Amino acid sequence: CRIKQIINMWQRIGQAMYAPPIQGVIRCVSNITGLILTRDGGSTNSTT
Amino acid sequence: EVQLVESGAQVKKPGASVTVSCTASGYKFTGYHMHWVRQAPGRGLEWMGWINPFRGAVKYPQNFRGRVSMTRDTSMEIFYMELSRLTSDDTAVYYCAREMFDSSADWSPWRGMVAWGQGTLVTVSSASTKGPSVFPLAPSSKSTSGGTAALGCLVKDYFPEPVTVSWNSGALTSGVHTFPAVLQSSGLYSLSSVVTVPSSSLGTQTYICNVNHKPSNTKVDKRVEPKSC
Amino acid sequence: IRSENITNNAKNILVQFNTPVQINCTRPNNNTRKSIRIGPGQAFYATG
Amino acid sequence: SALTQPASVSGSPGQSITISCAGSSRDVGGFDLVSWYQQHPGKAPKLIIYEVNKRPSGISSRFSASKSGNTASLTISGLQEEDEAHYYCYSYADGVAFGGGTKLTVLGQPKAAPSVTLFPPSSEELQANKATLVCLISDFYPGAVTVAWKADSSPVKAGVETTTPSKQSNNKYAASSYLSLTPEQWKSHRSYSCQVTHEGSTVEKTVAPT
Ligand SMILES: *[C@@H]1O[C@H](CO)[C@@H](O[C@@H]2O[C@H](CO)[C@@H](O[C@@H]3O[C@H](CO[C@H]4O[C@H](CO)[C@@H](O)[C@H](O)[C@@H]4O)[C@@H](O)[C@H](O[C@H]4O[C@H](CO)[C@@H](O)[C@H](O)[C@@H]4O[C@@H]4O[C@H](CO)[C@@H](O)[C@H](O)[C@H]4NC(C)=O)[C@@H]3O)[C@H](O)[C@H]2NC(C)=O)[C@H](O)[C@H]1NC(C)=O
Ligand SMILES: *[C@@H]1O[C@H](CO)[C@@H](O[C@@H]2O[C@H](CO)[C@@H](O[C@@H]3O[C@H](CO[C@H]4O[C@H](CO)[C@@H](O)[C@H](O)[C@@H]4O)[C@@H](O)[C@H](O[C@H]4O[C@H](CO)[C@@H](O)[C@H](O)[C@@H]4O)[C@@H]3O)[C@H](O)[C@H]2NC(C)=O)[C@H](O)[C@H]1NC(C)=O
């Protein structure tokens, strides 16, 4: 994993947020519950 | 107006990789898909993929996948595209083009490309600067049926392209069909240009061929004269 | 498995699980935070 | 290309012509994403039709298109000289499919047999450790032929290169071919030939050393 502090989330240029740092070691745990995926293209027809 | 303005044409060695820039203007940059398309000489169009400028999502074909690297500089409004591992087959004029409507619309990005880059000619060949050797193309006594004689010259083993061919310092323009530059299997270019001259003038008119090769600096004017039998 | 349109590979595909997947994420680094005085009232939190 | 177009279409100026684009049910039949593009030679392509039958803003009412099953069709009425260009059809097939491109011209000119002529490689080249043969073809119609090479009766595909026909000052086209060899390959064979076959009519020529 990689950590960034200067953030432009929602990509809106002109305005960026700098997240301050968090003290000590960080830990968190989450239920993965869904996904967002993209397919491919025509390529070979029906092979895979 | 919008405007897709692409980078300059580039002359490159095989095996390498090459990027093309295509700078957009005149619309919401980040909201519109951008396709890249090459068109090999005389050939059809090869769709190479596309980018969504919001966070940079992409999708390439199976053929072009691996070689293509497609990006955009939302800050600068420049699209970049890089085919890599260039082969002689990767010689084409490369375009960027925008789909009809913005990304918010349905079925974008598959509608149809409207704004079109000027094309960027990328040329993949392995040959090098070589002084051309010019020889004359002499018609024959059996090659005349009706009373005319077809002649010309040949510009082969020259590199790079092109080589323009006139006639008699510009005094003979009637019946001149100069053919388009094609690559040999070796890479040294080859060409030809014809002229239809009358057979009654085969003793009374000199037919010279001006062949110029600017990079190699070997300009050979080869006179085309009858093969003495 | 829901997608507005699957024939359209471009349409993102959203997945819903019946079972959650656990994931354990850490920043395994005990972090110092310096607070820097640019004020009046303005203070910047750096990393020690 | 995954979409099949006519190679070339000839129409009399003012008439009406039609270009076909046939694909599987995967693209043309099951989708309304058929779109057509015009490209003037040596220019960027240009969109003309989409959604099977839709004109972008700036497309004359002479231009119209449609799809009939798995075969879409593009139509132009009242043709004019500005329309002499390359035309490619498009449809989405999970990726991007494309038509091979069709050439547009003027109709009403008689057919012409290929004017074929052949010469041997000069001693200016035979002494240059090279031997090259060139096959000239001009004054012909329609503009779709095939040039061959036969060393005696045995063909040699090595060094075969052929250009793109150029429509000339006489509406007839002109194209050429080339064959790379060696002076040993030149002085060893009995004869070198160029066999040109137009519309089922073969025109062949032959040369030999000295
Ligand atoms: C991230 O890293 C930071 C930095 O290391 C770390 O925080 C440190 O945590 C430790 C442990 O809590 C702190 O140590 C303290 O040291 C005090 C003495 O320090 C001197 O003396 C020792 C020798 O003993 C030397 O080695 C050292 O160099 C110094 O000279 C000591 O006072 C502290 O312990 C008492 O105080 C705390 C509360 O303040 C309490 O938690 C302790 O239990 C203890 O209190 C006493 O407990 C006993 C139980 O037996 C009880 O009987 C008695 O009543 C209590 N008395 C009192 C008065 O409360 C402590 O050990 C160190 O200073 C911290 N540093 C910093 C910069 O914060 C984080 O924990 C790390 N975090 C992570 C997530 O890793
Ligand atoms: C993504 O969403 C689209 C719709 O938004 C769905 O696409 C449909 O897909 C099917 C199959 O590809 C297409 O159905 C076929 O279309 C033929 C003609 O289409 C015309 O007529 C329809 C009205 O039915 C119009 O909506 C359309 O604009 C066209 O004018 C019909 O001839 C077909 O019926 C016959 O053929 C098929 C096999 O070819 C048989 O299964 C049938 O039983 C029958 O014999 C057929 O209906 C349909 O046109 C597409 N709709 C649209 C609006 O484009 C996708 O399915 C969806 N993706 C997913 C994964 O769900």
Image (tube, rainbow, N blue to C red):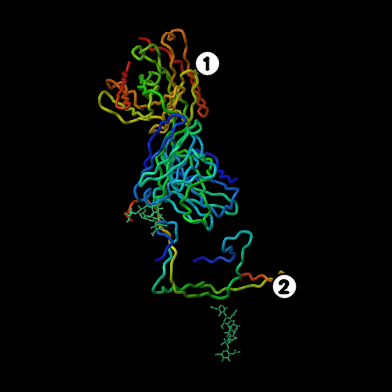
Residue B157 in sight here: no
Q: Quadrant of the C terminus of chain D?
A: top left
Which type of secondary structure does the marked residue at label 1 adopt? loop
User: Which residue appears at 45% of the width and 48% of the height?
Assistant: D51
Q: Amino acid at mark 1?
A: Ala
Quarter holding ligand 2: bottom left
Q: Nearer the viewer, residue D159 or D148?
A: D148
Whether discs 2 and 1 lie on one chain: the answer is no
Q: Amino acid at mark 2?
A: Gly
User: Which residue appears at 47% of the width and 22% of the height?
Assistant: D169
Instruction: Point out residue D95 in the picture as x, y percentages from the top left corner.
Output: 41, 51
Is residue D186 placed above or below B204 in the rendered structure? Answer: below
Residue B4 in sight here: yes
Q: CA distance from mark 2 to mark 1?
A: 86 Å
> Label 2 crowding class (10 Å Cα cut-off): few <14, some 14-19, many 20+?
few
Which type of secondary structure does the marked residue at label 2 adopt? loop
Residue located beneath label 1 in the image = B171
> Label 1 crowding class (10 Å Cα cut-off): few <14, some 14-19, many 20+?
few
Extreme residue in the left direction: D153
Is residue D209 placed above or below B20 in the rendered structure? Answer: above
Left/right of residue B169 with respect to residue D162 in the rendered view: right
Q: Nearer the viewer, mark 2 or mark 1?
A: 1
Q: Quadrant of the N terminus of chain D?
A: top left
Q: Nearer the viewer, residue C27 or B147?
A: B147
State which quadrant residue A9 falls in: bottom right
User: Which residue appears at 38% of the width and 33% of the height?
Assistant: B185
Mark 2 and mark 1 in contact? Answer it, CB < 8 Å. no
Instruction: Point out residue C3 in the picture as x, y percentages from the top left corner.
Output: 42, 63
Residue located beneath label 2 in the image = C41
Give the tally of numbered discs. 2
